[PDB]
Length: 284
RNA sequence: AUUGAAAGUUCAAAGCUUAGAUACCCUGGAGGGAAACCAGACUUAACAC
Image: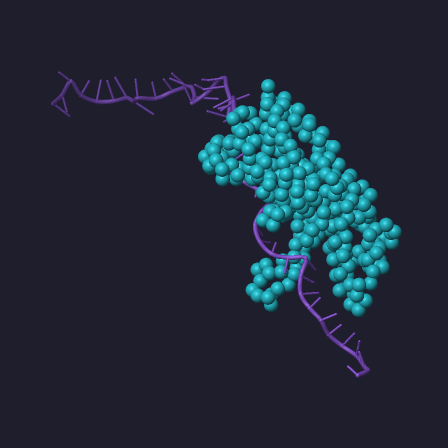
């Protein structure tokens, strides 16, 4: 119902790790995309909904539609700040998940290699995925049932494989990861954030001026507020296999490829990671 | 005016009976939601002199 929508911001502020962030952002996107309408005596006349203060601020009393536009921009920034502040990491379910999965893989007689990597700068993984896409035009790869951002197993595998190509040749890359005729020997799980020092998300901006622009006459900043993954967030994922003589390349490839980027726009130093730990458990 | 003349190969009769398109068979293997992008531009007006 509509009261769900008028209260979604309060619910974000008061649950902070226990609401579905995916659906929460999807719902508050309706508020963001009907902002001018949710501010015509249709705030349910509450007292905690952040929609109140946008009746108290007078940004432009001359023209009301401009006023609603500026209020909407302020509200976009405020939604970004809200999500970054309130939605924090509780990575105990993640440690439980990875420990149980490790036991499962041990029972299946796999050699497990559990890798912990910490982000060093603000990371962008899944920038074209849907999360905040309907508010920010930019997304984060988000698992809506772990209720966490994550790094897909396919990206980790692809980055490791492109490095192993660039180093040991396409033939060894196919001897490890397979081709259209043989299946790979190395399995990757998704990477989930297990611990953090502070905020899990933070706001950021990109402001292209001269992107696909003829001349300075075409120049104009178009700022893009969006969410990123805060620094010092540790992610964890597993690497399991059976054939022993495939652990050597993996071992070598992990420390290097994380220094270079792992998500989006690493060319300007965004998605850089440190190797926090690597443990190897040989099936005995 | 012939080793001739005359004489229906005819009658009755079900290609039926029993019989499973079934058995074995992973939509799988390979594949980075990435690439590009300045949170920036600029002071103006009024009167006094």
